[PDB]
Amino acid sequence: HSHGLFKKLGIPGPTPLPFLGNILSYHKGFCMFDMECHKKYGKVWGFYDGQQPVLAITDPDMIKTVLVKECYSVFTNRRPFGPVGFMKSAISIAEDEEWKRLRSLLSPTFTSGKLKEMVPIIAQYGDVLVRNLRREAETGKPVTLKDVFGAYSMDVITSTSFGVNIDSLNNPQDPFVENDPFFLSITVFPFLIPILEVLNICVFPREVTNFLRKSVKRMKESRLEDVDFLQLMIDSQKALSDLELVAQSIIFIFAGYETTSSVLSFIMYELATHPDVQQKLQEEIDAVLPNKAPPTYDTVLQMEYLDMVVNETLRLFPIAMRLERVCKKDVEINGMFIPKGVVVMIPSYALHRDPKYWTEPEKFLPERFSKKNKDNIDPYIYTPFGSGPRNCIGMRFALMNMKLALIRVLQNFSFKPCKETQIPLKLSLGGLLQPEKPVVLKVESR
Amino acid sequence: HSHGLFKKLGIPGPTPLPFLGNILSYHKGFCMFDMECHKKYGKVWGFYDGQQPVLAITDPDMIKTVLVKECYSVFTNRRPFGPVGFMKSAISIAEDEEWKRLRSLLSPTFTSGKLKEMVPIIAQYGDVLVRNLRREAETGKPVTLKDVFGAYSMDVITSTSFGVNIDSLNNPQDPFVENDPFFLSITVFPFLIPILEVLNICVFPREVTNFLRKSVKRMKESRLEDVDFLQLMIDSQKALSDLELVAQSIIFIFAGYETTSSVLSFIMYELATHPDVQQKLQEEIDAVLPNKAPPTYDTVLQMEYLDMVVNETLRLFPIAMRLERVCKKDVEINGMFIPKGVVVMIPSYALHRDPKYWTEPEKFLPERFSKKNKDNIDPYIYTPFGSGPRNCIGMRFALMNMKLALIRVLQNFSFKPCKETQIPLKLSLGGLLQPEKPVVLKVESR
Ligand code: HEM
Ligand code: HEM
Ligand SMILES: CC(C)(C)C(=O)N[C@H](CS[C@H](Cc1ccccc1)C(=O)NCCCc1cccnc1)Cc1ccc(-c2ccccc2)cc1
Ligand SMILES: CC(C)(C)C(=O)N[C@H](CS[C@H](Cc1ccccc1)C(=O)NCCCc1cccnc1)Cc1ccc(-c2ccccc2)cc1
């Protein structure tokens, strides 16, 4: 049932199987499925995740209506995701007015004013990065980036959100970095989510969160009385609740961990397989920060090829892959009727690799984003941070944390591929925008 | 979990058991449970139907805020009720804007103008009533009212809603009158409703509704081309859908059946155990309609003791027992904070029998509603039809259908109790406002 939806509206798509929908077509991954569907069906198409209708839209005018214009009136939420337990109050999982209050109350945390105050702290573990790096460099052994970056990425979270100062790679024992068949059974059995929920099963392991919950309550009452995300949520509390504040901490911790380290690894793959771009970036760094001067807030925004390199990697590897909004009312946007209940989905990975909006889309060409060519880029085809009132609230912090890392790591080292390095990088066919094989590179000391 | 709700708000109530809530206290019925809770806990209290918090309110100012004032903004819907299938679109089960459109689109059906046109049709089966009655009267055998009334009640539905003219008691074969452990398992297992729904299990037997669905589609396309509820929904179709129209037919059919016949039986019990009121009512009928004149629209509204007798029966037996609204937002009405999610419930049966607002509440005293005493009655303690934008949409049709019946049946007969008649009437301890033993009376010919 409901599988006749798109056949009634005149919207093309793959014919679904009973019960399953189209999820069998996920056998080559989310990204390859969207890329094929765009080629064969066109500007708009639909499919089913179980009994769930999802409408893919690629018209950049209609993407602005969803993500920006009618965000507050029709497209406010993302598709339901459970069982979640007390993480119902996480800002990325909240809906409607509860999100709006959390967005409003958590928004002042990522201002450039606050973000500028994070600069010295993020600059402390950029020095612990180089140090550990040189050590491994001397060992002349190939290096796994996702580890050395993940450790750096956790080092910057603990500090930025709780003031917990750990050298997580050399201090593995302290594991703030505690951090498939299941969810597909959940899409075909959405009727079973209330089964788990009333049993306190949660997609987030209850031992991690119970550790953070009592950890946060220890930091709340230690700093009361005695520059981090917690201080900013502690001074905010309509105001913040105590368990609510525990739920935002977990979102921030992950976001600053996986997203930062995963993107920083993609970047250094591209820089290692395109040495000209690495030398050009290193030339720019030493023209802005000579004598290996330490990056400051104003110097990092001053570096343009750093932004082009960052932006272009995000084009080839937008770690979100898709953006989604639920349609909560009957609506007709840009000449198309969308019924209440449909998940409107923007295929970000596919749009970033569309030969209509990009020349040689499979190529790492940072000049795409040069100041003479960025005016050509449509802001609704290239959405690595989403858009509209529900975009990535940590976009400014993420772009600054990575660039602060890149400047310090490339002021001291240069990265060359290894024989066991995977060229070309084949993406993991699974549900995360990750490499099939972890990224390994040679590292030498300038 | 959630069972600490009313203990956190300072609201009294019975202590719930795990999983079950207070439903074990339903062992003497909905009505006796509310009456006890009002006596022991006061003006406001709370309990749990499973994990569902329900807040009972008896303050008539606060009842106006829920049923009338903040109906459109906070208290628009009744508590979820499933599995229902395609009856999701029934006007009594719809929610928010979908109800508002159906209420607006079905409202012109019950105007006094249309209701006045129903008078001759309802007057045809009032004559089939007397006839069948005299027959049984001659047999000098005690009479079961719920049968002879239910047959009359079905006769008036088929006619009023489809033009199907049947003597349902003498024509049992044609069964438009096709019409517990389950629902209590559903309140403790609300997580299982999606299990049944995705299996097309429906609390309404799928054979009845599939018979009406194709029956309605036969009448729709027979009268297109060729004074009933269907003609009025056929001319209305934002406009009505075809399956939607099938769902409203089923609500109307039942409402006009059970409610009309069940109340008409309670009335004739009271008139038989209070012969003075019966003679006084019969005296009034013959002063307005002499020579057994046929009731017309203007003569029935002209009869006041008929309204007092009708109203008073509804006080002693309000067939709805409770009114309910879901609280869809945090709110503070009349100095009390009600959180999003709580079912606000008005205990109608209990309020009708409160010794604060009624003298000798256990007594059938129609003078309660005499023109000199009705100004004393608070319209929010006495709510046999609810109140506010979501009251009974068929109140006018129901009050006219019964009174049209009463005038014709008492112009020709008088009713006396039998030895097997239950005095006093003990109400069914189950979940419906019905007698424990069906009502039987002697019937003699004037
Ligand atoms: C390379 C790094 C990152 C990328 C590419 C990225 C991308 C995204 C995207 C595409 C969205 C959805 C936007 C939409 O639906 O329109 C999102 C949401 C979000 N991001 Fe990020 N993100 C990154 C890092 C971070 C960081 C460091 C934080 C730190 C707090 C963060 C916090 C969030 C939150 C809380 C949301 C949900 C906000 C809401 O729904 O209101 N992200 N991100
Ligand atoms: C003695 C006869 C009747 C009584 C005492 C009665 C009582 C009630 C009550 C108390 C409600 C709920 C009001 C509220 O929640 O505020 C209701 C709703 C309703 N009644 Fe009746 N009723 C009767 C007969 C009828 C008849 C003949 C119809 C014919 C169509 C009908 C149609 C409805 C409908 C459709 C609703 C739901 C309306 C909505 O929620 O918008 N009822 N009734
Ligand atoms: C933003 C993003 C990820 C696109 C998102 O909105 N995703 C939705 C919401 S859920 C997810 C829960 C969560 C929170 C914290 C830690 C772990 C998990 C969440 O809140 N992310 C935001 C916080 C961190 C962040 C990440 C990226 C950018 N910015 C910030 C749905 C989703 C995600 C994955 C699968 C899925 C994955 C694999 C296999 C099958 C299904 C299925 C559904
Ligand atoms: C108005 C009323 C009844 C108070 C109502 O709103 N009830 C709700 C909604 S459901 C019910 C479905 C329905 C529709 C048509 C035919 C059958 C059933 C419905 O729509 N009624 C309105 C139409 C007819 C009508 C009746 C009375 C007055 N006016 C009109 C919830 C409800 C009812 C009974 C039990 C319950 C009962 C027994 C045991 C356990 C639980 C549990 C929950």
Image (cartoon, coloured by chain):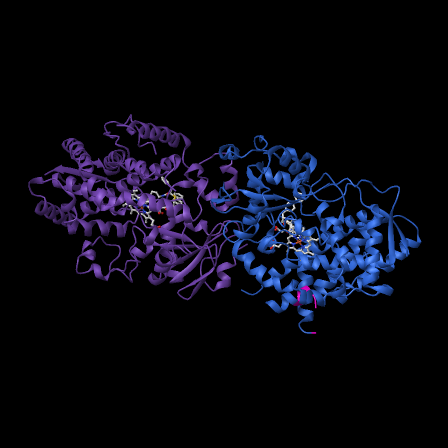
Chain colours: A purple, B blue
Pick the front one: A413 or A222? A222
Give the farthest residue toward the top.
A173
**Left or right for B92, reference A3:** right
Task: Please report the residue visible at 41 percent of the width from the left and 66 percent of the height from the top.
Answer: A335
The picture places residue A412, in percent across and down from the top left corner, at 12, 38
**Magenta-span inclusion, residue A116:** no
**Left or right for B326, reference B426:** left
A410 w.r.t. B160: above or below: above
**Left or right for B69, reference A379:** right
Which quarter of the rendering shows the C terminus of chain A?
A: top left
What is the quadrant of residue A180 in the picture?
A: top left
The picture places residue A162, in percent across and down from the top left corner, at 28, 33
Give the farthest residue toward the left.
A291
**Left or right for A306, reference A325:** left
Pick the front one: B372 or B226? B372
Task: Please report the residue visible at 55 percent of the width from the left and 45 percent of the height from the top.
Answer: B62
Q: Is residue A98 visible?
A: yes
The picture places residue A420, in percent across and down from the top left corner, at 23, 39
Which quarter of the rendering shows the N terminus of chain A?
A: bottom right
What is the quadrant of residue A177 in the picture?
A: top left
What is the quadrant of residue A231 in the picture?
A: top left
Q: How many marks?
A: 0
**Magenta-span inclusion, residue B227:** yes
Q: Is residue B175 visible?
A: no
The picture places residue B437, in percent across and down from the top left corner, at 80, 42
- Range of the magenta residues? B226-231
Pick the front one: B90 or A314? B90
